[PDB]
RNA sequence: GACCCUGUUGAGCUUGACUCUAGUUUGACAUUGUGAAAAGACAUAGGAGGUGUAGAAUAGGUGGGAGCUUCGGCGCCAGUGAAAUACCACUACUCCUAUUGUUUUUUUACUUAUUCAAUUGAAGACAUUGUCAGGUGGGGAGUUCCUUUAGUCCCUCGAAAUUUGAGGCUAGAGGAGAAAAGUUACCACAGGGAUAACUGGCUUGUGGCGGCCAAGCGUUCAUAGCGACGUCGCUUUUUGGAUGUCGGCUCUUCCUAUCAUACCGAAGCAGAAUUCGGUAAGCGUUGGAUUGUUCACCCACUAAUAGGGAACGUGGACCGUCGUGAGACAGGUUA
């Protein structure tokens, strides 16, 4: 049943992506590593060595959180999320980081540590809420240490 | 290797290698079934007569 | 049969059972299938040229000089420029940061050219959440008059103020007001504009929650709110002016409760409104009758826009005239 | 465009010269009337193609990139005054030396960019005189062919889908004569086993090609995906349209039965006929088969123009 | 929409005049007879036409969001800061201009101070610290800043040496999105 | 060093009271008329309609009603539809026409209003003016209820082919005064506090998360519970480039975690060539292309041209001066 529910999600992603792929202008804005190297030419630096989530690729930051630089290789946009009901783990995207209890500063940059609540897209699950509505964003607590092992693991708070 | 470049302790580097070597290990262990097929078709291909269509 | 068609469509596209049934009804069967392809399919990316700081040709030359693959889109627009490929990100170009061009959609273009804004004219926008419409209207009056930007959410207002002051508009005041209350505040405008909160079936590519999260209850309160939104538009405009001023009704939905029903309710309750040819180059006429109910034949002058015919979002445009 | 396998590419070039162009043998008694160029990829492929045609008996000159200053003049002199019939260039020797009015062009290796094909066929069929241009397409070189369709905007036919395909306007792909290909690949394998020097040139150009495969600019994903379908499609292995309608009939009466041999699926692999026997049963259970409405005036298209 | 007092009036025009050449065109009567007036909302000041200022008096004070063009912000210590919203009028009649090359144009958009290796051409009569407004080749307004060193001293530094400071750049429109 | 704190400065965040009102503003009504030309609205009287879909169809609608019946056309029926056609019975909208009128505007003028020169001329029904009904009000004068949640599904206003939305009412919880205040795991500056510093039975080959199973032990027992090996779901699948200072060479010595050479064990290992493993350090152990430099890959030679150790073998540092939205100094002496 866990294989069947994972197959239904994976098959649904397959036909949408294969049959309905349409050419669109989509390029990635340049990193903040070369942005700071340009700025420094224009140990004083402060660089975050914890795993982060950002969202929109090419944005300017507020001047409060602008000395901090988050490298490209420490970013994750997808997490492995377990649902205690139906006992299924899937990959769903991370929408935002809600609260990091270790540091309220780390909440603002979106530092992914243990017991950190994130918002995840539960569209592929299709869990039916009250009033016959399909969920789009739930709480999920991170239950691993993503700095030590590369994968980000989480459980849905349902 | 990107993760290791920004690491900050010997514990962190130890845990990151074990993840990488472990993740490549569980990929090969999943590949068990086709490896037996390719071993058996290798034995039978080498034990096949040589036929040259041109002659 | 029809019932097999509804169950198969809801299974393969993932729509709700209700909204698939409503959308299947307004189309012929093969036309419905071609519509379901397009509205799920992402739409082309379109650029509006700021007339104030630049114009169509020299901006086009500048972006190709930065590696952006463009093409002038249609004979409809002297202001629109389609994009096809771009090495540099679109928001990264220094032309963007000065405000030479702004990201828009096609459906954001046509209400503004449905309006005919002139110089030294007092105008309005009850919902200017992305701010593209407001910057387009100010491009037509050439930095004159006054625009009253309005949006009921402060979070969207920050993007409004950022977009307006980058584009160099200098003539717009932005207020966080519920637009039902707005004619009590001022009234007496020339050319009012309304982009109502809508069901969002016209654009599912940007917002894919309407696939299921839109039910019977939502289809009663939401068109109900457009009515109080729309009756305020007549009750705020001027019956007479030195330059004649007109209302424009623009919704991002293809639904029939949201569109062609609200305009029937408005033209019945206020007899001092007429509707004439809306000035957009193309389109499809509105339906005079949908489900046993008759609308006045002025709706043949209204224009409906569809994803399958044009690569645009689903849209309704109608323009009003005030009499008394 | 002819569908050839990698092991029959040399014999396929011998078909085009022998029975498609009907080139004369030996030295010819202001170019010649036949005057066929041969385009390839690497200087090691030049040395094979030149030295094989000397053993074939055709008059061939050759120029490549790091060829000597004096050596380049004498061979482009010989081609221009009509003392030889075949000129073998890679692409860089082509764009350096001056090319006269040319009749036929052979593409031994398919150009990676579709615009390189234009540059090659631009060297021929100019000034109102008629011309021909043949290419040996492969399975791995197929996506570069479907990308050539999208650039020229032409229609593609597969073997004998049309009775009379238009060669000058439509892209026509297919297979060569089966019988005469197996004779002239027998000759290639006979010469390869006989003389050591050509055999040493094969081993050099085998590893030279393997580098060229790795560094070639890859084709697009849509061209890559659409290549899988035409391989599956029944027109890929059918006889080419030049060879006539009369050649199509006895090919049809045989391959209508032969294609059922190729489409066979074994219900039992020979290891089923132990732990390995349970393994063969384990795969087949896991991997068994799985059960206009737009106006012409305004339609924002995802393609330019 | 409180208009500025006497003390607040000298502060805004002072730092304006350290960047402006003709202060009389800004406050000048135009053809319609209505002038440009300065109001302030929520400790930030706005530069507006008087007529649109007059009909802006209808909105409630702690309810109105923004109005016309923001000249800058009143700080808590009573000083005045410029924002890039002030740039369209500031670059309209600027007094010292700096042109930077395309490889130095994007550094300003990312937010670096101007270094010697990017300047396209300079203007003279610049003291050791003078306000200046930066453009590319096409005279597109990119920002404003203060000259780091004088007419002689700025160049005798290294080609890796900062020649003009960063104060504000057009890239801050890319933040509030 | 990190790290904690104090003061100044930025980025904010939350406030900064109530009632009339200056100012300012929206709408309405008057002076403000007299003609012409048009246009529009309604007042009545006529004429004609109608193709979202499907249905054969240019279906307003509605009451019934199954041959009313001239031909048995049309019917009945059947479909198809939200609604179905025969039959009689009713009345809606639109577009025209008319006069069987009330009007309202726009334009064009004039002055019969109104405003200036004058103290008779021009503008000209424009302004302008005043009164009601509003919006705002950091200003002037005095003065010391809202927020969060639920219900009455009760009343009022809306909307809907019968159910909703917005107000009203009720009840669980909160409360020296435009001069300036509280807060931040925040920024820049100045200062204060704290560890003399790291490892020395460290390190290596087999990932994390959740579920199932589970011998034992335990608060009293395998159920307060801790829990390996496996297996399942995610990463992960049905068509084959990465690297900052360093080197470069010779030489000595050691380890083995062995590339070669010696020996064995196993493999459809026929032969040839190998592959995996084990004992083994006696004996040997490269280049080239490319590179900032190396590795990866590719190419060539060779028996092979393994990897490491030798306290990682032997040949600035502030201070002062001027700046403060940023920055510097032919500035200093000293480490």
Image (cartoon, rainbow, N blue to C red):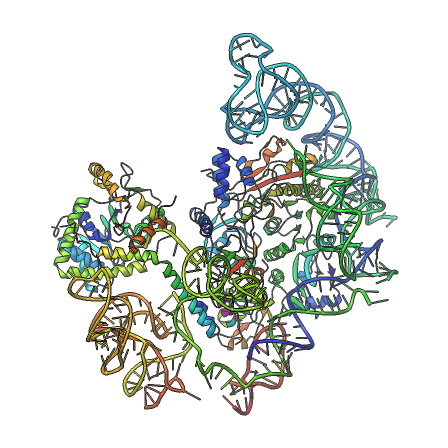
Quick check: C24 above or below A64? above
Residue toward you, A88 or C10: A88
Quick check: F101 above or below D147? above
Residue A108 seen: yes
Q: Position of residue F32 (x, y in %)?
A: 81, 38
Residue E78 seen: no
Q: Position of residue F206 (x, y in %)?
A: 40, 67
Q: Quadrant of the C terminus of chain C?
A: top right
Q: Quadrant of residue F37?
A: top right
Quick check: F44 above or below F3? above
Q: Is A28 one of the magenta-colored residues?
A: yes
Who's the residue at 74% across and 61% down the image?
E3
Q: Position of residue E10 (x, y in %)?
A: 71, 68
User: Could you tell me how many numbered marks the image carries?
Assistant: 0
Q: Is B43 one of the magenta-colored residues?
A: no
Q: Is residue C222 left or right of residue A20?
A: right
Q: Quadrant of residue C319?
A: top right
Q: Is residue E32 left or right of residue D50?
A: right
Magenta-colored span:
A23-39
Residue toward you, D82 or F333: F333
Quick check: C14 above or below E81? above
Q: Position of residue C297 (x, y in %)?
A: 61, 31
């Amino acid at each position: 049943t866990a294989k069947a529910l994972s197959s239904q999600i994976k098959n649904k992603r397959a036909e949408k992506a294969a049959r309905f792929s349409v050419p669109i202008p989509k390029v990635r804005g340049i990193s903040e590593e070369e942005m700071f190297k340009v700025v420094k030419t224009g140990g004083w630096k402060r660089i975050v060595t914890k795993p982060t989530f950002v969202g929109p690729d090419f944005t300017r930051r507020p001047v409060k959180y602008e000395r901090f630089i988050r490298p490209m290789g420490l970013r994750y946009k997808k997490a492995n999320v377990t649902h205690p009901t139906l006992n299924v783990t899937v990959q769903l995207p991370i929408l935002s980081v809600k609260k990091n209890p270790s540091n309220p500063l780390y909440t603002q940059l979106g530092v992914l540590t243990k017991g950190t609540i994130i918002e995840v897209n539960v569209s592929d699950l299709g869990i039916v809420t009250a009033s016959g509505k399909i969920a789009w964003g739930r709480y999920a607590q991170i239950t691993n240490n993503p700095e030590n092992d590369g994968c980000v693991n989480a459980v849905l708070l349902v | 290797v990107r993760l290791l470049k920004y690491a900050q302790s010997l514990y962190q580097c130890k845990q990151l290698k074990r993840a990488a070597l472990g993740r490549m290990a569980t990929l090969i262990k999943r590949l068990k079934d086709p490896l037996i097929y390719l071993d058996q078709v290798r034995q039978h291909l080498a034990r096949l007569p040589d036929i040259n269509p041109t002659t | 049969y029809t019932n097999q068609l509804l169950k198969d469509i809801c299974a393969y596209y993932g729509y709700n059972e209700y909204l698939a049934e409503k959308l299947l009804n307004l189309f012929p069967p093969r036309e419905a299938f071609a519509f379901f392809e397009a509205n799920e399919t992402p739409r082309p990316v379109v650029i509006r040229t700021n007339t104030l700081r630049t114009h169509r040709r020299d901006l086009a030359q500048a972006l190709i000089n930065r590696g952006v693959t463009l093409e002038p889109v249609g004979k409809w627009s002297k202001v629109g420029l389609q994009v096809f490929d771009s090495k540099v990100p679109l928001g990264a170009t220094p032309e963007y940061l000065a405000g030479h061009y702004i990201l828009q959609a096609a459906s954001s273009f046509l209400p503004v050219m449905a309006l005919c804004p002139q110089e030294n004219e007092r105008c309005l926008d009850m919902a200017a959440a992305p701010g593209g419409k407001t910057t387009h209207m100010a491009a037509l009056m050439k930095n004159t008059g006054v625009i009253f930007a309005n949006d009921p959410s402060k979070s969207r207002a920050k993007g409004l103020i950022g977009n307006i002051h980058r584009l160099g508009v200098r003539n717009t005041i932005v207020c966080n007001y519920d637009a039902r209350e707005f004619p009590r505040v001022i009234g007496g405008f020339d050319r009012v504009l309304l982009d109502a909160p809508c069901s969002g079936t016209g654009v599912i590519c940007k917002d894919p929650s309407v696939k299921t999260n839109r039910d019977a209850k939502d289809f009663m309160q939401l068109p109900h709110t457009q009515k109080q939104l729309l009756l305020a538009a007549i009750d705020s405009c001027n019956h007479a002016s030195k330059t004649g001023g007109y209302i424009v009704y623009s919704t991002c939905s293809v639904c029939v409760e949201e569109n062609e029903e609200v305009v029937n309710y408005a033209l019945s309750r206020r007899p001092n409104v007429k509707l004439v040819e809306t000035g957009l180059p193309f389109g499809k006429e509105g339906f005079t009758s949908y489900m046993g109910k008759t609308f006045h034949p002025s709706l043949k002058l209204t224009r409906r826009f569809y994803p399958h015919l044009y690569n645009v979002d689903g849209f309704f445009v109608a323009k009003f005239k005030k009499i008394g | 465009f002819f569908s050839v396998k990698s092991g029959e590419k040399e014999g396929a070039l011998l078909h085009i010269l022998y029975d498609i162009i009907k080139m004369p043998l030996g030295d010819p008694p202001k170019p010649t009337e036949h005057s066929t160029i041969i385009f390839t990829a690497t200087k090691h492929h030049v040395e094979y193609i030149s030295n094989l045609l000397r053993l074939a008996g055709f008059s061939v000159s050759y120029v490549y990139g790091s060829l000597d200053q004096t050596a380049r003049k004498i061979q482009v002199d010989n081609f221009r005054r009509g003392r030889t019939n075949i000129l073998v260039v890679t692409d860089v020797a082509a764009r350096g030396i001056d090319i006269p009015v040319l009749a036929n062009v052979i593409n031994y290796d398919f150009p990676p960019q579709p615009k390189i094909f234009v540059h090659r066929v631009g060297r021929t069929a100019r000034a109102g005189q008629r011309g021909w241009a043949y290419a040996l397409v492969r399975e791995s070189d197929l996506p570069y062919l479907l990308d050539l369709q999208l650039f020229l905007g032409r229609r593609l036919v597969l073997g004998r889908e049309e009775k009379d395909p238009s060669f000058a306007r439509d892209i026509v792909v297919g297979s060569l004569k089966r019988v005469e290909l197996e004779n002239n690949v027998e000759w290639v394998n006979k010469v390869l086993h006989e003389n050591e020097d050509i055999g040493a040139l094969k081993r050099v150009t085998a590893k030279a090609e393997k580098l060229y495969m790795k560094t070639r600019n890859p084709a697009s994903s849509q061209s890559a995906k659409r290549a899988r379908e035409v391989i599956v499609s029944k027109g890929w292995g059918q006889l080419h349209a030049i060879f006539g309608e009369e050649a199509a009939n006895e090919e049809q009466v045989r391959d209508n039965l032969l294609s059922k041999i190729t489409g066979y699926k074994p219900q039992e692999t020979i290891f089923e006929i132990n732990k390995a026997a349970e393994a063969v049963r384990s795969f087949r259970q896991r991997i068994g088969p799985r059960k206009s409405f737009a106006d012409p005036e305004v339609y924002m298209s995802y393609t330019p123009r | 929409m409180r208009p500025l007092t006497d003390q607040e009036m000298k502060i805004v025009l002072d730092k304006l005049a350290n960047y402006m050449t003709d202060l009389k065109s800004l406050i000048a009567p135009l053809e319609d007879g209505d002038r440009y007036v300065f109001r302030m909302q929520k400790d930030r000041v706005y530069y507006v036409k008087l007529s649109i200022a007059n009909i802006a008096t209808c909105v409630a004070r702690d309810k109105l969001l923004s109005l016309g063009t923001c000249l800058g912000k009143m700080t808590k210590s009573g000083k005045f800061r410029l924002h890039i919203t002030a740039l369209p009028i500031l670059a309209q009649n600027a007094r010292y201009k700096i042109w930077v090359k395309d490889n130095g144009a994007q550094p300003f958009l990312y937010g670096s101070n101007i270094v010697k290796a990017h300047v396209g051409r300079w203007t003279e009569d610049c003291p050791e610290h003078s306000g200046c407004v930066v453009y590319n080749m096409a005279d597109i307004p990119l920002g404003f800043g203060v000259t780091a060193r004088s007419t002689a001293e700025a160049r005798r530094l290294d080609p890796t040496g900062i020649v003009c400071f960063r104060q504000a750049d057009c890239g801050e429109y890319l933040r509030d999105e």
